[PDB]
Length: 49
Length: 49
Image (tube, rainbow over all chains, first blue to last red; front, side, top):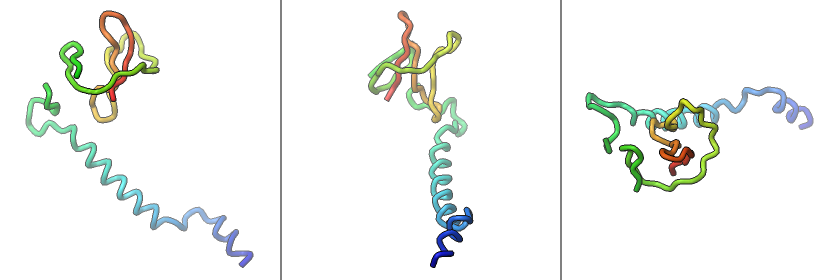
């Protein structure tokens, strides 16, 4: 029980699964946000103009 | 609502603290939309929210 704490503390690559879950969610949201900039064959991507 | 030199939109305006350079006209955010604008006539900078 003494050794397990420092064993956990030393290694920085144990929580990878949760890390990838969060990263995938964030990347999907970021791509969805970015998609709004396309012109899609139109004159401009802004509706007001 | 606002209309600045043909640029139209709605939102609130506040004193922006950016260090705009003399050759810069208007600022725009990460989503290619106008965030801060250098005011005409008298030269000030305001942000849009």
